[PDB]
Image (spheres, grey):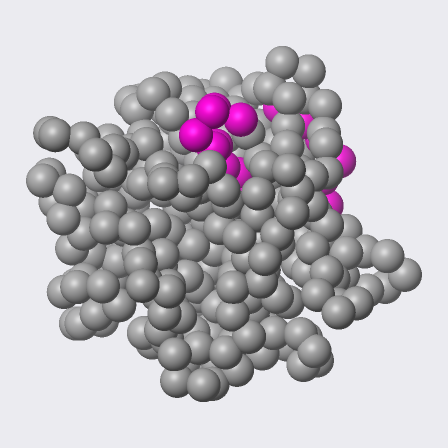
Amino acid sequence: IPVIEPLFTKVTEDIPGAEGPVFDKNGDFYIVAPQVEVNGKPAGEILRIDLKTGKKTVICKPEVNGYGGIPAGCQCDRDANQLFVADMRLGLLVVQTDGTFEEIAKKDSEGRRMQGCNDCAFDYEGNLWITAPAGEVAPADYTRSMQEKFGSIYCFTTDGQMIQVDTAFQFPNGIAVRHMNDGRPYQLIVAETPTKKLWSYDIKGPAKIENKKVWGHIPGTHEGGADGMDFDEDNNLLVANWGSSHIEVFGPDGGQPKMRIRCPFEKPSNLHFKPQTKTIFVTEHENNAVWKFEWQRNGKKQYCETLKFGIF
Ligand SMILES: [Ca+2]
Ligand SMILES: [Ca+2]
C-alpha cells in the first residue's frame, strides 16, 4: 500500500481533544474542544480559528441546565450559516456564529431518550446523518460504547424528525455520505472505531438505510481506529486512523486502503477540506493541535457549498 508524506503545516495549538473541523458559508474556520473541563465536569467549547494568526476564540461553551457539553463533530448548514454540532452529552445542537445555540432533541422520533452524538454528515437532500457512540444525553450519567455495543445512528430529517436508523455499534464515530454524480445520496459510511471497520448502507431515501455491510478494513491492532472521515471530489474516502499515525485513503469500492498518508503525529482525529481547495485541515490528539496539508485534489462539495435555487 503506497504511503505519501505531504508537508503538514501548523494551524493552531492547545485545543483539548481537538475535533470537528468545519468551514462555514463565509469561509470561516471552526474547531471543537470536547475535553475542556471545569472542576472535573464537562465544559466543552466550540471555537473559531483565525487562519491568518492561528488565534483562537471560544464562541460557544454549551451547557443545558448546568450540564456542560462535549461537542465533537460539525457540519455547516446551507440555507442558513449555522453549525450542526454533535455533542456527546447534549445530543445534536444548532450553533450560530454569534455564539448562541439550541439543543435539538431530548428524545428521538420514537419517544426514546436521545443518545450523545459524536459526528454528523449532511447529504445533498439536507438530511443529517449522525453517529451516537455515547449513552443517553444529560442529565443521565455519562457512558460511551467503547466496550459494549450500544452506539446508535440517527437521521435528522428536513421535516425535523430525529430518527434512529440503527443501533448496536461499538462506538460509531466518523460518518460520510456518498452521492451519485447527479447529486443523489446513495451510500452511507459509518466508522466503528475499536473494531477497525467501516460500515456501509444503501440510502434508499430520507432516514431509510438498508443492506448493512462491512465496507472497509482499518489497518493496525493499536488502540483506536477510524475516527473522522471525508470524501474528495473523486469520491475517495480519507479516514483518520487514530493511533496509527496515518490517514487511510479508500477507493469508491472500499475494502483495503489504496493509499495511506503519514502524519507527523500518532493520533489523527478528524479532517475537513477547505472549500474550493486541496487543503485538508486535520485535528490530532497527540499534541491537541490543528494542522493542514495538501491532498491530491479538491474535496467533495459539502452540503453547505451546494445551491438550493441553483438551476444546474
Ligand atoms: Ca470523532
Ligand atoms: Ca469533516
Q: Answer whether residue 65 is magenta in the image.
A: no
> Which of 174/81 is in front?
81
Residue 153, percent from left and from top: 39, 69
Quarter of the image with the N terminus in it: top left
Residue segment shown in magenta: 10-28
Residue 134, percent from left and from top: 56, 71
Q: How many marks?
A: 0
Residue 39 position (above or below residue 97): below
Residue 198 position (above or below residue 232): below
Q: Is residue 293 visible?
A: yes
Horizontal relation, residue 186 to residue 98: left or right: left
Q: Answer whether residue 19 is magenta in the image.
A: yes
Q: Residue at x 31, y 63 (%)?
A: 159
> Which of 225/161 is in front?
161
Q: Residue at x 79, y 67 (%)?
A: 66
Residue 259, percent from left and from top: 31, 36
Horizontal relation, residue 290 to residue 169: left or right: right
